[PDB]
Amino acid sequence: LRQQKLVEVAKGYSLVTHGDEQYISYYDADGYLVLGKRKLNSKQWTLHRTQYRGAHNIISIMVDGEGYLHVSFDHHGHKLNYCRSIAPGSLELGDKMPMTGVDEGNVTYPEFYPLTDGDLLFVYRSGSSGRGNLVMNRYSLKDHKWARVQDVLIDGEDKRNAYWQLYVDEKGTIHLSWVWRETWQVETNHDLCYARSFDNGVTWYKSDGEQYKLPITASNAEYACRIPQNSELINQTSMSADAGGNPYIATYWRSSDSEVPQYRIVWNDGKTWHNRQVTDRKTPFTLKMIPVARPRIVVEDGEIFYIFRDEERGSRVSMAHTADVANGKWIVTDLTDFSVDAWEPSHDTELWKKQRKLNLFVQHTCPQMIYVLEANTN
Ligand SMILES: O=C(O)[C@H]1O[C@@H](O)[C@H](O)[C@@H](O)[C@@H]1O
């Protein structure tokens, strides 16, 4: 036990590195939104209880190129809740403020991403039409303002909803993938679709270089994988990309000849889509507490670290690792030797891109101690 560390934060009911500091956000026992930071390679957190008290309880944070922390949280799912630190490096937040002042009345699932040269992307689920719709904004560091990038990017044309995940790669390309859902029931999830943008969201492409004419519907979407309804396909997972801009999507579903849903990796190598089963599960479950977690991935030129949690492994924090997604065997290990129950993984996206260090937000999930697990990957 030389390498890996389980670093205490504090007890609670995202995680992002900027420079040599790691920031964290969580709700304490009294329901207050807390912002914290540490120097990397130390275990001392500075923890700041904010003035804000808590699509139930979601917090997204990101630091811009000037070092300001941007924070958005979703409690009630109505008006946008968005704040910014008072100064570079500060954990103190200002008053709530608008972004564009348009379509900010029915906001859930806020998400920030970094863009090239210190700008930020913001994506949220807008309910102002009556159904969830992906709305995308950009924060320009040179004029210190938010602008709308797309009002309608994925269009379910009154027949369906979309559940998306995004990743901004090390070259500044925005990757987007999603599943469709036909009705209120989770069993009506189907398919995995893809798009990417090289120009901060103005123009979108398929992986084969064909340009989309927006909006993207079920008819014109690129299908990374055709997966029918009633396949135990989960919605709202995650995706990543390697340094070469190839996308990787982590999710799970059941093949038509099995009763057992399996973790999957779906990726495009520049020529075609592939998918591969990640572990060798034996225990059936249906979505119609889910016994497995939505997965997270980090990648290094085809080498994958695939983080999950499964009742078959005692609900530990688990990892599947392959040296090469195309040809190598998966090695499956547990990063903890204790159960974290209903935990789902999240990781410090920026720390992996900048330093190739994998840090996970770990907490026993039904006040429980929050930890940063510093995993070994090389
Ligand atoms: O240069 C920047 O600010 C950002 O550029 C983005 O494309 C990268 O994904 C992010 O890791 C960088 O921090």
Image (cartoon, helix red, strand yellow):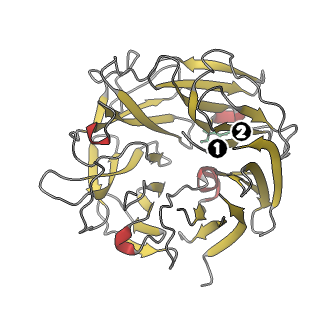
- For badge 2, the amino acid type reads Val
Q: State which quarter of the image contains the N terminus.
A: bottom right
Residue 60 shows in the view: yes
Task: From this view, report whether residue 214 is shown above or below residue 341.
Answer: above
Residue at 61%, 31% in the rendered image? 122
Q: Are marks 2 and 1 in contact (CB under 8 Å)?
A: yes
Position in image of residue 301 (x %, y %): 45, 55
- Mark 2 crowdedness (10 Å alpha carbons): few <14, some 14-19, many ≥20: many
Front-most of 176 and 25?
25
Ligand 1 position by quadrant: top right
Within 8 Å of ligand 1, the CB of disc 2?
no
- Mark 1 crowdedness (10 Å alpha carbons): few <14, some 14-19, many ≥20: some
* Numbered mark located on residue 71 in the image: 2
Direction from residue 361 to residue 42 in the image, left or right:
right
Position in image of residue 15 (x %, y %): 65, 53
- For badge 1, the amino acid type reads Ile
Within 8 Å of ligand 1, the CB of disc 1?
no
Residue lying at the far left of the rendered structure: 257
Q: Secondary structure at mark 1?
A: strand
Label 2 – label 1 distance at C-alpha: 7 Å
Front-most of 45 and 274?
45
Residue at 69%, 16% in the rendered image? 101
Residue designated by label 1 = 59
The mark tally for this picture is 2
Task: From this view, report whether residue 28 is shown above or below residue 128.
Answer: below
Residue lying at the far bottom of the rendered structure: 1
Position in image of residue 228 (x %, y %): 20, 39
Q: Earlier in the sequence, mark 2 or mark 1?
A: 1
Q: Secondary structure at mark 2?
A: strand
Residue 300 shows in the view: no
